[PDB]
Image (cartoon, rainbow, N blue to C red; front, side, top):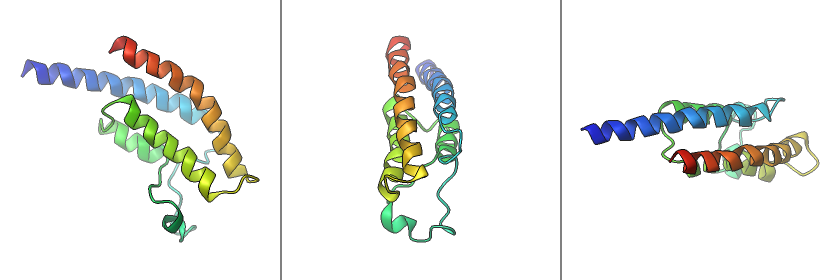
Length: 121
């Protein structure tokens, strides 16, 4: 149908906007702490601690399959990155600290993204 196509153009454009959002958030991680999945070879107990691992590469795979229906779903995954880190790692670690700084800096980007998603519809 023509409606299904219209719907698909909307999703494509959301994917376009979320791709730009993801790039802006990932720039706030210049150490690349959150770039890839925590290695289960190197942290073998990880899934005993963290039930839903997340990282920027995994988000990008979902994004490119157009697997985010709305900004809320995307935000859920970004929050997992931060929240998983802040639980597994102690306060006095470079990892925790990196997550705090990513959360604080990401807030700004995500604030305007929400406005853009509502604005453009």
